[PDB]
Each structure stands twice: as C-alpha cells, then as structure tokens.
Image (cartoon, rainbow, N blue to C red; front, side, top):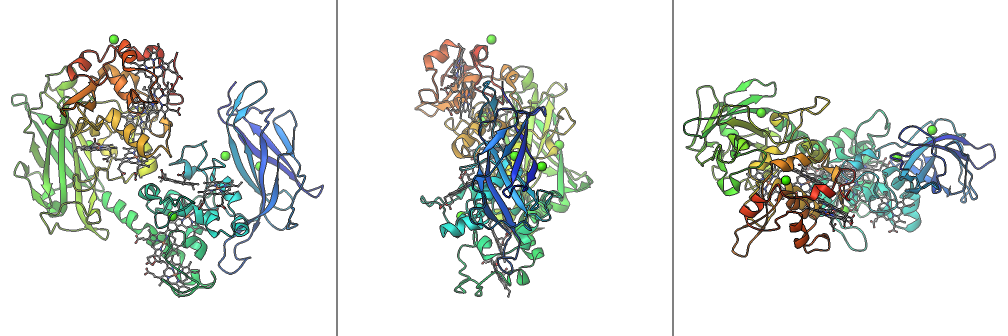
Length: 627
Ligand code: HEC
Ligand code: HEC
Ligand code: HEC
Ligand code: HEC
Ligand code: HEC
Ligand code: HEC
Ligand code: HEC
Ligand code: HEC
Ligand code: HEC
Ligand code: HEC
Ligand SMILES: [Ca+2]
Ligand SMILES: [Ca+2]
Ligand SMILES: [Ca+2]
Ligand SMILES: [Ca+2]
Ligand SMILES: [Ca+2]
C-alpha cells in the first residue's frame, strides 16, 4: 500500500455551536477516499485583519484563533474537527475572513499503506461561506521551482502558506522580533545584505541564485487577487529586509518616516515594479534581438570542418554580420567529435574566438552572403573511433557589447570580459557534420534538459559568462528533437565539446558532463537538491552507457589521467570509493567488471564489462532500487 498524493479539502465550516466545526475530505491521486489518517491537524486557525486597519499603509495580517488535533474519522474520507480551546484571546470577529491551515504528517495508515505529507489553507467568511476578501500574494508552487517539493523548507512545513500562517505579524510582535514576520524573513534569507540566525549565515548562495529577482516568487495570477502587493504595499517592515542600512526612525539613509502612511505617495507601484525588474527585463530584451543559424560541412579530402554562422533578427530574417561586427564582444566555436562519446578530449578539441571586441580573427572571414566562416585547424580524427566518430559537433557561443539595456560598439579591443555589466551573452548554437555525408549521430537529450536548469538559474542563464567565455544562452536554436508532446528539447549535448570523457583542463576535476553537474550540485546545491534526481532528470538513459567508453575520474601523482568504466565513474561522483558514501570496495567493484581510477586503455577495454545493472534498477523516483 502506497498513496502517491494526499488531497485535502475543507468541505464544511459550521459555527452553529460557537467555535467552528471543520470537516476535511481526504482523497488519493485516484480521487478515492483516504480512511484512517492518524496525524491530521488544524495547525492554525486565523482571521484576516484587513490592510490599513492597524494604520495607514500597513499590511493585512493574520490574527491567531488557535489550533486543534481533536477530530473524528467519519470512516468515509471525511474528518470532523472540534476546538477544545478556540479563540483563547477572545478576538473572534465574524465580519473577518477566517482561515484554516490543515496538515497531514507523512506516515502509515493502520493497514501499513504509506501516506505522504499534505498541507493546505482555505479561507471562508465568518459563517463558513466563501470569503469576501483575501491576502493571496504568492502560492507554494514558486518555492518548488528551487526547493524540493514535499520536503521541509528549513523547518516545520513544506508549503509557503503554512509558513505564512505561523510567521505572522502577531507572532513577531509577541516575540519582540520584527525580522521573524514572514514578509521580512522571506527576503532576508535570500538576500546577502545582512546575515540571519544565531550563526549569522550570510545568504551568499541564495543571493547568487535569486539575485533579488521579485518575479521568481511574485507572479501575476487570476488565482491570487493580491499578487501585485509586492509593488502596491511598500512598508518599512518589508522594504528594510534587503534595504538594511536605512534607519527610518532617525532619518539616516532616507528622510524620517515614523510610520507607513506616506510610502505609497512617493513609491508608486509602477516605479517599485519597474526599478526592481528593469535590468533582467533589459537583458532578456537584448538576448531576444538576434539569433544565429549555424551549419557545418566536412571536406571529404582534408577532413576539416567549415562552420558557417548566419545572424538573424527577432523575426528570423538574415542580418549581414558586417552590419553588427563592431558590437560583437566575442564569438567562439568549439568542435569535438563523437557526440555520444567525445574522442578529442579537452586538449584536442578545436576552439577559436572567431570575433573578439569587434575584430575578426585572421582565421575567420565574413563571406559575400554576410555569414561568418571558419575552418577547423586541429586534427578531428574523423572515423578513427567507430560509427559515432563520423560526426563532428560544433558549439557556437557569442556576446554583444551592451550598456544600460542597449547594444554598443566595442571601444576597447583588449576588453577582458571580467565586467559582465558591459556585455550580454546571446543565444548559443550547435551544428553537426559527417565525413561520410551520412546523417549525423546525435547524443541522447531525453533524460536532462535546460527547462530543469532554468527552474533555478532562469531561461536567461549566460553559462560561463566572464573572462574565459562569451556566455552560453541555451535555447531551441540548438534543439534537434522533440518530447512525446512535440515540445522542442533544449539539450546540454553541446556542453560535451569541453566536458569530454577525458575531462576539462585538468584530469582532477571530473570534467566529463556525466560527472560535472552531479559534482557541482552535490557540493553546492545539496540544501536544495539532496538526493532529488528529479531536480534535473525526467528519466535515466541507462541505454546510453552502451555508447560510452572510459570516463576520467582522477589525476595520477604525475598529473596524467586516471579513468573508470562508465557506470562506476557516473555513480562514484556522489559515492566516492573508500568513503563513508560507498559500501562497495575497489576490489568488489572490480569483481563486478569495473576499472576504478586505472589507465584509459584498461577502462576502455572493460567499459562494457560492468554488471552493475544486473542488481541496480535505478529510476528517477528511486535511484537506490537494487537486489
Ligand atoms: C530559486 C530561484 C529559489 C526560489 C524560487 C526560492 N528559493 Fe529559497 N533558497 C534558494 C537558494 C539558492 C537558497 C540558499 C541555499 C543555500 O544552500 O544557502 C535558499 C534559501 C532559503 C532559506 C534559508 C534556509 C535554507 O533552506 O537554506 C529559506 C527558509 C527559503 N529559501 C525559503 C523559500 C520559500 C518559502 C520560497 C517560496 C516563497 C523560496 N525559498 C523560493 C533558492 C530559491
Ligand atoms: C510555527 C508553527 C512555525 C511554522 C509553520 C514555521 N515556522 Fe519558522 N520559525 C518558527 C519559530 C517559533 C522560530 C524561531 C523564531 C525566533 O524567535 O527566532 C522560527 C524561525 C525560522 C527562521 C529563522 C529566522 C531568523 O532567525 O531570522 C527561518 C528561516 C524560518 N523559521 C523559516 C520557515 C519556513 C520557510 C517555514 C515554512 C516552510 C516556516 N519557518 C514555518 C515557527 C514556525
Ligand atoms: C521568494 C524567494 C521571494 C522573492 C524573490 C521576493 N519575494 Fe516578496 N514576498 C514573498 C513572500 C512569500 C511574501 C509573503 C506573502 C504573504 O502572503 O504574506 C512576500 C511579501 C512581499 C511584500 C508584502 C506585501 C504586503 O501585503 O505587505 C512586499 C512589498 C514584497 N514581497 C516585495 C518584494 C520585492 C520588491 C521583491 C524584489 C526586490 C520581492 N518581494 C522578492 C516572496 C518573495
Ligand atoms: C530584496 C529582495 C529587495 C526588497 C525586498 C526590496 N528591494 Fe529595493 N532594491 C533592491 C535591489 C537589488 C536594488 C538595486 C536595483 C537595481 O537594479 O539598481 C533595489 C533598489 C531600490 C531603489 C532604487 C535605489 C535607491 O537608491 O533608491 C528603490 C527606491 C527601492 N529599491 C525601493 C524598495 C521599496 C520601496 C521596497 C519595498 C516595497 C523595496 N525596495 C524592497 C532589492 C530589494
Ligand atoms: C517621498 C517624499 C518619499 C516618501 C514619503 C518615502 N520615500 Fe522612500 N525614497 C524616496 C526617494 C526619492 C528615494 C531615492 C530614490 C532613488 O532611486 O534614488 C527613496 C528611497 C527608498 C528606498 C531605497 C533605499 C536605497 O536603495 O538606498 C527604500 C527601500 C524606500 N525608499 C522605502 C520607503 C518606505 C518603506 C517608505 C514609507 C515608510 C518611504 N520610502 C517613504 C522618496 C520617499
Ligand atoms: C536548483 C535546485 C538548481 C537546479 C535545478 C540546477 N542548479 Fe546549477 N546551481 C545551483 C546552486 C544553488 C548553485 C551554486 C550557486 C553558488 O553561488 O554557489 C548552482 C551552480 C551552478 C553553476 C556554477 C556557476 C554559477 O552560476 O554559480 C553552473 C554552471 C550551474 N549551476 C549549471 C546548472 C545546469 C546546466 C543545470 C541543469 C542541468 C543546473 N545548474 C541545475 C542550483 C541549481
Ligand atoms: C569549453 C569552452 C567549455 C564549454 C563549451 C562548457 N564548459 Fe563548463 N567548464 C569548462 C571549464 C574549463 C570548467 C572548469 C574546470 C571544471 O571542469 O570544473 C568548466 C566548469 C563547469 C562547471 C563547474 C562550475 C563552474 O566552474 O562553472 C559546470 C557545472 C559546467 N562547467 C557546466 C557546463 C554546461 C552545462 C555547459 C553547456 C551549456 C558547459 N559547461 C560548456 C569549460 C566549458
Ligand atoms: C542537475 C544538477 C542534475 C541532478 C540533480 C542529477 N543529475 Fe544526473 N545528470 C545530469 C547531467 C547534465 C547529465 C549528463 C547527460 C549527458 O548528456 O551526459 C547527467 C547524467 C546522469 C546519468 C547518465 C545517464 C543519462 O541519463 O544521461 C545517470 C545515471 C545520472 N545522471 C544519475 C543521476 C542520479 C541517480 C541522480 C540523483 C541522485 C542524478 N543524476 C541527479 C544532471 C543532474
Ligand atoms: C549525486 C548526484 C548522486 C549520484 C550520481 C548517485 N547517487 Fe546514489 N545516492 C545519493 C545520495 C545523496 C544518497 C542518499 C545518501 C543518504 O544516506 O542520505 C544516495 C543513495 C544511494 C543508495 C542507498 C544508500 C546505500 O548505502 O546503498 C544506493 C543503492 C545508491 N545511491 C546507488 C547509486 C547508483 C547505482 C548510482 C549510479 C547509477 C548512484 N547512486 C548515483 C547521490 C547520488
Ligand atoms: C548485486 C550483486 C550488486 C552488483 C552487481 C552491484 N551492486 Fe551496487 N549495491 C548493491 C547493494 C545490495 C547495495 C546496498 C543497497 C542498500 O540500500 O543498502 C549497493 C549499493 C551501491 C551504491 C550505494 C553505496 C552507498 O551509498 O554506500 C552504489 C553507488 C552502487 N552500489 C554502485 C554499483 C556499481 C557502480 C556497480 C557496478 C560496478 C555495482 N553497484 C554493482 C548490490 C550490487
Ligand atoms: Ca473547500
Ligand atoms: Ca498542498
Ligand atoms: Ca539577509
Ligand atoms: Ca541551430
Ligand atoms: Ca557486456
């Protein structure tokens, strides 16, 4: 027995006896009644003090009426709560909106059926009818973009409405701690201007992901009638959460404000909304002004790839590159071979900055058709490593010079790209060519795609933007397949040009794409992801292992490469051999056909000898499934 989803509805609220009687109906993912819940509770009963009631400019706030774990299982999927101690403070007002926060703890029914956590709020008028007014600003779904759905976020609960129901203005006032009001706390813990908690945690990582972008949590919605409160209700209590150096009482860093009466008179919604979103809006506008369309052909006699880049405008119309060359900050072309098992390594790949700060490299030209044209100089070794090695794949990244939301001419040929306020990474592209002239091989893209990355990093993520790279914006420009609904898949297959089976610049960094995303995110995003493979994966492509060879897993004492068989290499990124995270010894892994941190030749020869998937049957839902 296992329930996948527990749905909760408050179906009836009756005040016929004084204190409300509250009926909850519980169903599973199949809409069948759930009988026997043992940990159902009204975690909070509240009523809504309306906006301005506590003073001009002040927020609406949730006033406490108690809680209850007292209920009858009616044996039909419904549960009826009573309150032993309703409204201890004697503030109940039937003219106010009434809220109930209902939670069901993860656990087991009696029959042993597993039941997942469930939370909800529902609002009512003072007689249990539909409510007359609400404070509906955000919904739990925005938090699930970045925090694993169904797991506690910091503590107590899994859904933002539960946090909001306890972290009230009344709660903060009662503790003498303004900062624990949820509308203060939530900005505080994602903003690095001040630390939080006894430990003085500086939110460096939250700051680097969220970047004060109001629109990752504040989203307009017919379902959320107070969604525009983020710009319409300026208060010292909320604005000070990130604006930490103003003292409104003393008039330091701002004119004196003794209350919230005048904030909106000067801080109009249009200005607050515009000023906090201006820069991301302007950047997104610049990224969407141009595209590129890239082709690649192999000379059958020289075995060199020629890559052609067509700039296009927002409508897909040709732009001659000569017209915008002075504004191009960088354009880079990286070519590798064998899209399912890259063969040239990091050191052997072909790479060029065809354009730097408005100057063509002498190896790149613009033809009479207005296309940039570049021919590889490295030995591509086409056809030297089986059918996959027939195919060259070329990744194009580029950037435009930009200031205050406009493209500008490059004024400084030596501009180093460190100052990311001076340029915009643009839409990257991927082009395939074959030596044989047959259709190209392509890597699988059916297990991970850029939609998952964009949940935390946004669709405008300028990957590697800085001193070393233009910034790769990943879009349908480099899609070559569709999912089962016909949606273009934006794969990470182009990243393999550098993230090769031989690693990146050093044999020490687990640079292969099969290892690198796991290594970065298990080290730096475990608070968000932990073991949640679904944060990136729709599926595992286990069949892809049959196209892999050796994967670089370590550097020897002399700085040369050590390699593992590909399943062992992939699992060991998070399961280090000889650590507390890996039960299998090296000897045991070798008994299962593996090479652990051996020579490229030994790992290549053994790459299809691993018996791991005889026992292991990983799925995204449970990657641990085995024996
Ligand atoms: C991605 C853009 C995010 C969205 C949307 C939300 N949160 Fe977040 N949060 C995020 C990061 C990158 C971090 C820092 C993690 C780290 O490792 O340092 C956080 C941090 C928090 C915290 C602090 C405690 C913690 O879990 O580390 C809280 C309490 C928190 N976040 C809550 C939260 C809620 C309730 C959200 C929806 C309104 C929410 N976050 C959105 C990234 C993102
Ligand atoms: C009451 C039933 C709570 C619910 C639901 C949530 N939290 Fe909470 N939180 C609670 C208490 C009693 C405290 C200590 C307050 C104090 O006096 O210091 C907290 C504290 C936090 C903090 C630390 C805030 C700070 O020190 O600046 C965070 C980041 C926090 N709580 C987050 C949080 C989130 C995201 C919740 C919903 C998932 C949540 N809390 C619910 C009580 C209650
Ligand atoms: C998620 C990590 C958020 C980001 C980023 C920002 N805000 Fe936010 N805000 C968030 C929550 C969960 C809440 C509480 C909502 C509730 O129902 O209590 C808020 C609240 C505000 C408010 C208060 C509105 C009111 O009625 O008093 C304001 C003025 C506000 N938020 C503004 C704001 C701005 C300007 C941001 C970008 C700079 C922004 N928020 C980011 C969650 C998150
Ligand atoms: C963190 C999530 C923030 C909250 C909450 C609020 N603001 Fe903010 N504000 C923030 C940043 C990162 C910036 C710089 C933005 C940029 O692109 O330049 C700002 C800026 C302002 C400004 C302009 C700067 C100035 O010196 O006055 C104003 C007037 C401003 N912010 C007002 C404001 C108000 C009224 C808020 C509560 C509704 C508020 N901010 C919240 C980050 C955050
Ligand atoms: C008009 C007479 C104002 C009243 C009343 C309030 N504020 Fe203000 N504020 C005003 C100006 C002209 C500026 C500078 C704008 C700029 O872009 O330079 C501000 C600034 C702020 C900021 C930003 C602080 C910073 O980034 O340095 C915040 C967060 C802010 N103001 C909030 C705020 C609140 C909450 C008010 C009522 C208590 C309030 N301001 C009153 C103009 C006026
Ligand atoms: C939220 C749950 C995330 C998902 C999904 C993905 N990434 Fe991520 N990434 C996340 C965090 C919290 C951090 C560390 C930030 C810090 O400041 O330390 C990262 C880091 C990266 C980096 C490093 C560069 C950077 O901008 O910090 C890269 C290049 C990166 N992440 C890429 C990436 C890709 C391609 C993803 C889809 C496979 C991806 N991330 C998912 C949080 C999250
Ligand atoms: C060669 C021009 C590269 C391309 C194309 C991509 N990456 Fe990269 N990446 C590269 C180097 C030299 C390094 C540092 C050494 C190392 O292997 O760690 C990286 C690093 C990453 C990281 C780790 C964190 C960081 O340093 O930013 C991640 C998560 C990463 N790279 C992801 C990534 C993705 C998703 C790419 C396709 C969009 C991608 N890289 C392309 C070199 C190059
Ligand atoms: C985003 C930060 C990721 C998380 C979280 C996890 N995986 Fe992953 N995985 C990721 C990428 C970018 C790739 C490379 C795809 C490529 O083209 O090489 C992978 C690859 C795997 C593979 C190889 C098979 C495949 O589908 O490509 C396996 C078996 C795999 N990942 C397993 C896995 C497990 C078990 C996770 C949860 C603990 C997990 N991944 C998280 C990115 C991310
Ligand atoms: C990082 C992105 C991971 C990759 C890649 C893989 N695993 Fe994993 N695994 C990971 C975590 C964070 C955990 C939970 C650890 C804890 O105790 O909380 C696990 C757990 C397992 C387990 C269960 C633990 C045990 O002692 O056996 C198994 C069997 C397991 N993982 C197997 C496994 C295999 C076969 C992988 C390659 C296909 C693999 N994991 C990759 C994180 C990550
Ligand atoms: C059956 C005889 C097995 C073969 C063949 C392989 N593994 Fe295994 N593995 C097995 C069991 C019974 C367990 C523990 C399961 C549990 O829940 O406790 C494991 C565990 C792992 C783990 C998790 C390690 C940890 O977290 O400590 C990993 C990463 C793992 N196994 C990988 C792995 C690889 C790469 C194999 C082929 C070389 C392999 N296993 C073979 C059972 C069996
Ligand atoms: Ca209802
Ligand atoms: Ca819910
Ligand atoms: Ca802070
Ligand atoms: Ca293309
Ligand atoms: Ca075999």
